[PDB]
Amino acid sequence: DIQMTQSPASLSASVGETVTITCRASGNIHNYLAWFQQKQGKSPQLLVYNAKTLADGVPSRFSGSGSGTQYSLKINSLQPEDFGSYYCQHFWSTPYTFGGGTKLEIKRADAAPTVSIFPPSSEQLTSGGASVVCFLNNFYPKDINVKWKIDGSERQNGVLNSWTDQDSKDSTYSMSSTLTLTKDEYERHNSYTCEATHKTSTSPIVKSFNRNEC
Amino acid sequence: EVQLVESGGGLVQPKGSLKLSCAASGFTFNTYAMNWVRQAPGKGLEWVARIRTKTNNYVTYYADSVKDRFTISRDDSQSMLYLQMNNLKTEDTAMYYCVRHVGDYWGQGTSVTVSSASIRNPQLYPLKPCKGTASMTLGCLVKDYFPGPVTVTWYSDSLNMSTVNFPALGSELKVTTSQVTSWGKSAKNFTCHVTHPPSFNESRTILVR
Amino acid sequence: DDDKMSWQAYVDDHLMCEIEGNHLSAAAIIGQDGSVWAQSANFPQFKSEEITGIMSDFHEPGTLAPTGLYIGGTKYMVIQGEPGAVIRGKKGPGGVTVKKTNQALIIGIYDEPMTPGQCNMIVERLGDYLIDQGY
Ligand SMILES: *[C@@H]1O[C@H](CO[C@@H]2O[C@@H](C)[C@@H](O)[C@@H](O)[C@@H]2O)[C@@H](O[C@@H]2O[C@H](CO)[C@@H](O[C@@H]3O[C@H](CO)[C@@H](O)[C@H](O[C@H]4O[C@H](CO)[C@@H](O)[C@H](O)[C@@H]4O)[C@@H]3O)[C@H](O)[C@H]2NC(C)=O)[C@H](O)[C@H]1NC(C)=O
């Protein structure tokens, strides 16, 4: 069997720069190697089939190179839609082994988030539950901290935090903070605040009044 | 024109069996060799099986991981590919694609979860701004489901409609969030339609005043 | 049918590449009609009857054996192959492998220091690879 080792594991580059992902076989695959790009939540897509042949609808910024046991994929003039992971696969002999993948992040200018909070739904409230949801929509980098404060008292045990991949055109991340409680627990208090810390000049926040105004 | 549509995935208890299918349209299916490729939930890609054309006696090649359990077959009269799975282990939980030859065209994928747990159909909650704080952004909360995945799709009467879905969070009972963002002229209807694999379809409508 | 890779690129990068230190002596992708799709610099010029005899053996395995595998005026003794898929010949330390696709013929000619298994491997792989696209 021919196992394949890809490198590097992760690469970050500002738009306009150039990167190469190298892929190595344990034996001569005689230029039977293909390159695939994959984004989160979608199926892979062939970029380069055989050592150097580009597939249909692939930008010419992808140069497929290599011979023998070592091959590489060059992306000159990197564009913000090139985020994702890249896998190499050989077709010399079975098994047609894949690689480990290389996750490409797009280095980008810093941006601050936009926070928007939402109160528990009518249907969840009648179900015996209550979840205050908070959507931070556009920012870079992905590193960010969240603080749920009920009447100014901090709470950190029951909040779930979901992150997204980079935007196809903005290269900006997004995040969702959802704090869930019971109906008695949420109805006892009135003020709910959702605070985020990023660039750290100050924390953007939003608040609701638990039917005192809601 | 070329389209591969998988089906048959779902939740199965360990040591179970399952028969995935792949329907090919837009090309002469008899003249191509087909693949099954899987991807673990957080891990990378792995090639599992390949079948050949009638010219070489429909030869079959498997991966050692699934060597003596899995069976790949095809019905060229109906342009269908099949993957038979027996003695399903936890390590088989992944998304399965059919792939044509070297990867020119892949499929949408069919998800398969091998776990002792039981299916929990999701609960959908509409999240609206607080009275007076109305903004363009709206959304939906899908909570407490297993095994996944859920396909949350928006339908509205507005143009310039952006939809952002957030990756699911959890083992066993999982949750996920979806956000819509409208711009321009105001719209009256914002409906989110959530699908769970075992024939679960439900919708929540957010009307705006 | 994929038209994105030139047949010249196929013979150069999948038939005449280095395998186990050795190189094929010559290689070509030829149609079953007799039209050469691509060929290396030193691949011989076929004769029409030679291709028809090759094709008749693919249609009935064992019919070329009395005559021999005639390629470019050179006589190779037929040796064991795969029925309807591969035809092989030996001329002392050298030999030739003819692999059949749906529409074409992959041919590789070797001479010492090249083993017959290495010529078999390269030629037949490109054969199977192109059969799996319909070519
Ligand atoms: C708010 O929006 C939702 C979503 O509708 C979709 O978006 C809109 C912006 C618009 O483009 C719509 O055209 C689009 O569908 C609306 O909810 C949908 O409402 C329709 C009508 O009830 C449903 O369509 C149904 O589909 C069934 C099969 O899929 C079909 O059987 C139904 O017909 C039945 O009933 C009639 C009447 O007796 C009968 O003649 C038929 O023979 C059949 O029995 C019907 O066509 C959708 O499924 C709904 N949901 C979705 C996600 O589309 C909603 O109406 C709209 N407005 C408000 C106020 O909420």
Image (cartoon, coloured by chain):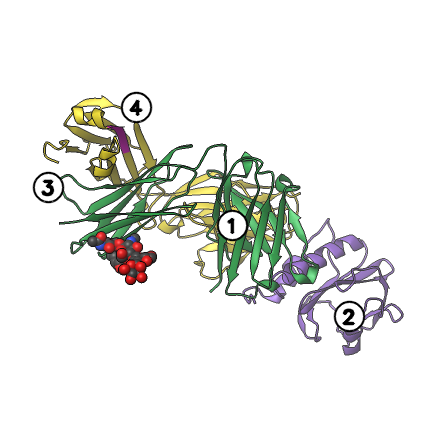
Percent coordinates x, y for residue B128 in the rendering: 20, 42
Q: Which residue is mark 4?
A: A157
Label 4 SS: loop
Within-10-Å neighbours for mark 1: few <14, some 14–19, many 20+: many
Q: The chain drawn green is chain what?
A: B
Left or right of A213 on screen, residue A197? right
Q: Which mark is residue B97?
A: 1
Q: Quadrant of ligand 1?
A: bottom left
Look at the image and give the colour of chain C: purple
Left or right of B95 on screen, residue B154? left
Which amino acid type is shown beneath numbered disc 2? His
In this rendering, the label closer to the viewer, 3 or 2? 3
What range of the chain is rendered magenta?
A: A178-182
The Cα atoms of the two marked residues, 4 and 2, are separated by 75 Å
Establish whether ligand 1 lies closer than 8 Å to the Cβ of label 4: no
Percent coordinates x, y for residue A138 in the rendering: 26, 42
Q: Is residue B163 magenta?
A: no
Within-10-Å neighbours for mark 4: few <14, some 14–19, many 20+: few
Within-10-Å neighbours for mark 2: few <14, some 14–19, many 20+: few
Q: The chain drawn yellow is chain what?
A: A
The Cα atoms of the two marked residues, 1 and 3, are separated by 47 Å
Q: Are marks 4 and 1 on the same chain?
A: no
